[PDB]
Every structure is written in C-alpha cells, then in structure tokens.
Length: 577
Ligand SMILES: *[C@@H]1O[C@H](CO)[C@@H](O)[C@H](O)[C@H]1NC(C)=O
Ligand SMILES: *[C@@H]1O[C@H](CO)[C@@H](O)[C@H](O)[C@H]1NC(C)=O
Ligand SMILES: C[C@H](NC(=O)O)C(=O)O
Ligand SMILES: [Cl-]
Ligand SMILES: [Cl-]
Ligand SMILES: [Zn+2]
Image (cartoon, rainbow, N blue to C red; front, side, top):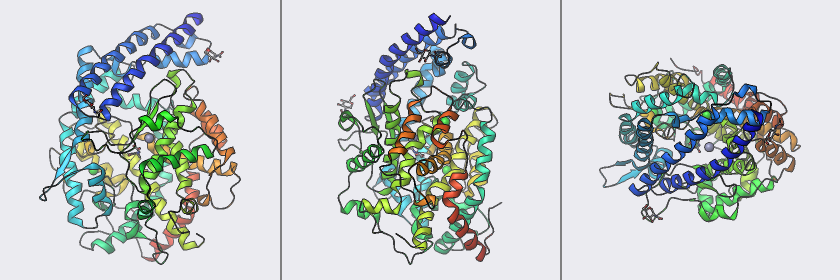
C-alpha cells in the first residue's frame, strides 16, 4: 500500500503539471481570442486532459484511502478519485464540453442593439449605462436588453447542462452537482453555518435597503418606488444590483462634505490598466509578499484588445501549473471599481505563487472562499480615504461626516452584496437537486431575488426569460457561494491583520500598507494550499478557527447606528413582503 501510494502521487503530480499546463494554454488562447480555430483546439485539449484524468482517476480508485498512514498522501489520492466531468462517457463528455463552450461564448459576444445604430457590449458599454444613467427608461432599456440578449440565449443550453453536470457528479459519488460543489469546503454544517452568517448581517442590510429605497423614492418619484415594498432591480447602478456603490451620489449621507471624482482623478493623472496593477503589485510587496514575475507583464491581457479580437472580458487570474507562468485576463477600465477588482485578481496571483511548490493536487485555496478574499483584504486598505489620498486620488479626512460617508460608500459595495452572493447558489443548489425544474427557473430566481435582496423586476418576466443566464457565473458554470464566504472572512482577516499591524481605533480606519507582520500571516496561510482543512488557515490568520460575521459587523458598526437613527426618524418600515 504505502510504498505504492507515495509513487502514484509522484507520477500523478509530474504528469498533471505537463498536461494541465497545455490545457491552460489552449484555454487561454480561446478566452483571449474567441474564434472557431481556438475553440476546436480547446475542445481538442479537453479530451486530452480528460484522458489524463481517467487514467489516474481510475488508478487512484484502486487504493483504500482510509487505510494509508500518511495524511498528505491520503488527501491527494482521495481528491484524484474525483474525475469530475471526466467521469462522463466519451459521448456525454464531448456534448458537455461543447455546451460549456457554447454557453460561455454566447455570453461573451452578446450585444444589445438600439435605435441609434449602436449595439452595446457588457463591458464597458452596458456597464457604464447602469452605473451612470439616472433615467428610468434608459436603465430599463439596458437592464431588459441585456437579459433579452444574454439571458434568453442561454436557456436552450441550460437544462442539458444541468443533466450532464449532475450525471458527472453522481458518477463521482455525489448526489448531484450542488452536493459536489458544496463538498469543496469539507464542512458538513456548511448550509447552516452560512444561513447563520446570513441572518447575522440582516439588520445591517435591512437598514441599508430601507435608507437607499428612500433615496431612490426622492430621485425617481413616489410613483415608481414603494417605501414598503421591494426596489426595482435596475436602479442600483450595477447590471445585477449586486453592489450599489455606483449610486453613491443619490444616497450621500452628508452631501455637505464634497466628493472627489476619483475616476476623473485617475484619468486626469493619466492612470492606465497597467498603472493600476503595478499599484496592486506594490501593495503586495509592501507587505513583504511576492511580486508578479516579469513574465506576468509580458503575457497578461490587462485591457480589452483593439485588434478586432473577440474575448471573454470578465476578470480572472490564471495558473499555468509550471510555477512561473501566472496571468490575469481583464478588460480593465480606468476607475476605482476596477482598481479594486485588479487587487482582487492580484490576490489570486499571489496565492498561486505562494503555494506553487506543493503537489498540483493541493494547489488550491484553503477553500474557495480564501482564494477569493486575499485581494479583497488589501483592497480594503486601498479604499480608505487616507490611502486613496496618498495615491493623490482624494484630497483628504477627519470629520465624522466624512467618516459616515466613507462607511456608506463601502456598505453599498460590501453589505449590498451579501444577500446576492447568498442567493445565486441557493438557486443553483435547488436546480441541481431537482426542486426547481426548467419550468420554474426564472420564477424561483425572482422569488429568491425578492426574499433575500428585497428586489423586484422593473419589467414583468415572461416565458423564455432566463435571467440567471444574464449573470456570468451561470453559463460559465463557476460556483458562486465562494464570494459570500469571501465577503464574510475578508473582514475577519482585515481585523486580524490590523491587530497584528498594531492598528488601534475603529477598524474601518485601518490601512495595513507596508505591514510586514500582516504579510507574514497571510503568506503562512496561503502556503498551506489545500494541504489542510481550512479551519487551520483561518486559525493561522485570525487566531481562531471559524467564519464569523463579528468582524464585518464591527467594521460597519458606526454606520449601523447612523442608519437606525436615520431610518427611525423617517419612520421607515424595514424589509418588504
Ligand atoms: C487569434 O486566433 C486566430 C486563429 O486561431 C489567429 O489567426 C490569430 O493570430 C490570433 N490572434 C492574435 C491576435 O494572436
Ligand atoms: C507523506 O509524504 C509526503 C510527500 O512525500 C510528505 O509531504 C508528507 O510530509 C509525508 N507525510 C507524513 C505524515 O509523513
Ligand atoms: C465579485 C465577482 N468578482 C470576480 O468575478 O472577479 C463577480 O464578478 O461577480
Ligand atoms: Cl436578474
Ligand atoms: Cl465555491
Ligand atoms: Zn475571484
């Protein structure tokens, strides 16, 4: 047993590195250049990797895992026994791979055309409309249009997608795909752990929702906003209403304290996509963490090409499984929002580099949530007025009004996102376990959109509509619940790192810039890769073992107080029906 396990892992590790690096490349070529040639080659390279997976997956399954004395070897072999999609029969595997490609290609090339000659794209066009327009009918056109284009187009695929991904899941020992995805956390109590967390952040959200619904009532008119009902999903400044920081202007707590146009600020001082990432790279190295290799700047696609190429714009980071080749693919726009997303992605790159010497099978985050949080943690410090001013993007600084305005801006981003990030997989886990048929896809999506977010669709939905497909992570088949976890624990890391950095005072005023003791804690944890259960990583960083919403509640605490008084004096009626 033991002698033969050890050897299997070594062979599996050295062959996977090669095969996976080739797949990455093909996959990279397609994402950054959507053509027929690059699609075929990608599909081609799918069968190769599936073959590698089946050879070692089958091998692995012949080992009695619970009877191996080594923990590191035992964890690797068990993971290898999960063939995932590769568990499917040749035929079903090729159909499945084609469906994923077709879904992701459909979403990435969809346009919404006008009567003004002009067809708009998600980035940056339709995104800019949702963030800057304050015209109900204009926002409605983009909101409805995008779903008419992307949403509708993904429906014909999805039912088959669900059938195939559940089969693949059952073929790997799980009940269905949701069960598979949830196991990535190795936490039986996951569902209930998360619902407790969600509930904890309820008062804070209900108070933000109500304060923002009042603001929108002020701007769009009583005839469009019910102060006792849900909010029209198209008025929050973001295509999916997942973050509401783009309508900061309509909800400024203290407008008497002026706001610097950070975007104008960045454009004026000539900030470019490259500059942004360089700044992100600087923050990481300031913490003593690793800088991105020169190769990174060479090969990355830090901005939407202009050579006619058609690409998958959505932000993502890439590991090429060779310990040197790491890239990021982002259609970066010059603004504060993307400056944060750039850090988020640089957070992924850092992780890749931190655990690049572990066996490939363990080259993952403690759990999906960790991978997602790293960059957001630093971004939290980058976003502080003080740090923003040191980048000459803000003028200041000091006043309680400037303090509450900042907390609001952050709340519009972080708090607003909680119910959404919770919702997405609540819908999918149910779709996967069969409680939601293709007959009720959309209806159930909006039941949850209302129940958790307090949102209603500006235009009644009709048969054929499949609004879930209008969200990247759906056709792209990327689990979403990792972001929910991310938003909870990033604050737990922020609070831990800040304590380490010697920060005293309100948590929201913390900036870990250049904190060596802070980078030391992150690095030690990122180094573990997936070698250990995540509670140990949570422990190395925060000094305890659990997710908790106390850090996030404490950060916003001042804002929570402000919100209660504010809503209370306007006789606001929290929540909806
Ligand atoms: C994109 O792919 C096509 C065909 O695969 C190729 O001809 C072209 O050179 C690639 N574009 C760029 C910019 O490299
Ligand atoms: C088992 O072997 C692996 C790889 O050689 C090693 O990383 C690990 O430390 C060993 N585990 C134990 C418990 O000895
Ligand atoms: C928050 C997440 N970020 C990402 O994909 O980089 C999203 O876009 O919905
Ligand atoms: Cl929607
Ligand atoms: Cl996940
Ligand atoms: Zn991410």
